[PDB]
Amino acid sequence: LEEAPWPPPEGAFVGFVLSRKEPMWADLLALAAARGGRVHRAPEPYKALRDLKEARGLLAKDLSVLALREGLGLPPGDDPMLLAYLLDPSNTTPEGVARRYGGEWTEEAGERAALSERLFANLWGRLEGEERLLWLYREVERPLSAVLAHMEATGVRLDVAYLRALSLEVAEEIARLEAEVFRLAGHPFNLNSRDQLERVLFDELGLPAIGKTEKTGKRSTSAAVLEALREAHPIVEKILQYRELTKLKSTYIDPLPDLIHPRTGRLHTRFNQTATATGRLSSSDPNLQNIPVRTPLGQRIRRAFIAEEGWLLVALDYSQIELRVLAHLSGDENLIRVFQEGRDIHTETASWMFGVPREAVDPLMRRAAKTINFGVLYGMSAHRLSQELAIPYEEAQAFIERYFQSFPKVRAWIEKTLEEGRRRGYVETLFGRRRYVPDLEARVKSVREAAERMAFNMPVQGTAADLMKLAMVKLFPRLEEMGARMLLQVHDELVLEAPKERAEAVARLAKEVMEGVYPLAVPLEVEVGIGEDWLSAKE
DNA sequence: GACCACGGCGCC
DNA sequence: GGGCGCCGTGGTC
């Protein structure tokens, strides 16, 4: 390689060492590039960030973020990382990617550009005759890296003072319970140590140990275990709530506020692109993809996510996309009809496996269809259905059958793909995204059967993902062409920011933009909500 | 302080 | 139970 004066030729391979992961808090320690066999090093990374029109290299989307925060647009472009993730969703980091395709991931912003190139090469080449895959990299992955980039920069408005209020009130409720339980033990004891509670519940108290842990195999103090001891002791209930409050506070009410960027007053997440096996996205430090919403407590927490004054929040959730995906995927004319007839799956499905005159008088039978559907999706075993839903391992066996009688192609599709899996060694989505599953031909019924569940769910997840992924890529442009922003994405639902003025004129659009991203043998339904905060946006 | 395994749990 | 990522507890360097 030959050392060259900073000014790099048009379209080189970037390379940069941050002072940490989160581009939003990091400091560009070093900036560099690599074209041909010449290494260009910026004596000053910040300024140099000006001589580039795009980010072409690993974690491209990342340097695009910092650039974005410094006022510079600098969009994210080509990126090996993205290509490997498509060839092998197992490929999730630069370290391993290089350590797998020729190169040592180093700490030099220059050795990195020199790694990227040779990597993009080795990789782009490897893409010989991979139409589908390549369609995803060009039509979805590369473009999306940008949408995310803006997503990260934009950040999210969070009502800190509020969350602070919660923290102190909660802190109290927690304490009242800590006292109650501590008494119920005739002596206090750290309540966060599952170990101490084991010795307290099972040993000290004569409570029946229902199960053990996987790794070490101790007596599990799990929620299921305890719920299963609801009746037994009263201390169980109270301990359950304490676990609730503690989770919510510790993981949300407390850590959130401090993560507010001082230069924005907004929460800046990290939406990782190549980190999932199904092609799903995932968010890091902080993860705003698990913001509570079920308990009263978690709902109040959701409130704390408001929008820039004079604006509003737009929440759009794809109505059960995985089932519909399956529908299109499977072919069960009987299932698809249910979705097309604009009928309530859990209601009609229920009205089928029971041969019940119409959809009448089945209050508990609808609680059923849900699990069967959300069961078949990842193959829930009849036993787990008995435990879960109240039924015997004689009815759980029949339900699975009565259900398939109605939806044959599902079963078929399951076995089809499964088979195909072992022959090929991987499974894919509607667009061609594949996930290798080696243990399909494993002798251990235990491991194999698991391999199957993993192996067969991937398509109805990866696909559903690609769907949204596409949508997100389609939408954003018209977004900016409207002055609105894309805040968060949660696998099958989105959250946007529009000004009170156009706010409602945006929903209508985003909806129809998603609903038809890639029409299927069924219609993609989408619910929408608008409000000053996440909870009220009717998410 | 930086960082690991593990049980436990929040969202999809 | 399919897919993620954060959190104390306990314990290492």
Image (cartoon, coloured by chain):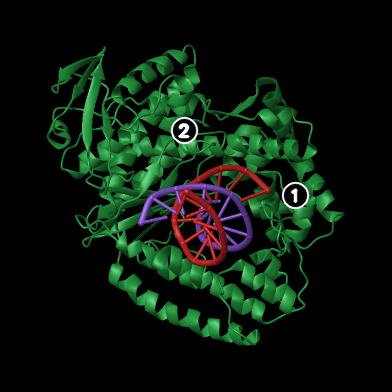
Chain colours: A green, B purple, C red
Which of B5/A224 is in front? Answer: B5
- Residue A292 lies left or right of residue A421; in this view the side is left
SS for callout 1: helix
Q: Confirm whether residue A533 shows in the render.
A: no
**Are the numbered discs 2 and 1 placed on the same chain, yes or no?**
yes
Tell me the residue at 49%/79% (across/down).
A174
Q: Amino acid at mark 1?
A: Trp
Badge 2: chain ID: A
Q: Amino acid at mark 2?
A: Tyr
Q: Is residue A434 above or below residue A532?
A: above
Tell me the residue at 66%/44% (across/down).
A378
In terms of image quadrants, where is residue A66?
top left
Tell me the residue at 70%/20% (across/down).
A423
Which of A497/A18 is in front? Answer: A18
Please state the horizontal and vertical placement of residue A533, each as a whole percent of the image.
34, 63
Q: Is residue A356 above or below residue A280?
A: below
SS for callout 2: loop
Which of A285/A402 is in front? Answer: A285
Q: Confirm whether residue A150 shows in the render.
A: yes
Residue annotated with mark 1: A352
For disc 1, the neighbor class at 10 Å (few under 14, some 14 to 19, many from 20) is some
Q: Which mark is in front, 2 or 1?
A: 2
Tell me the residue at 73%/60% (across/down).
A212
Residue annotated with mark 2: A518
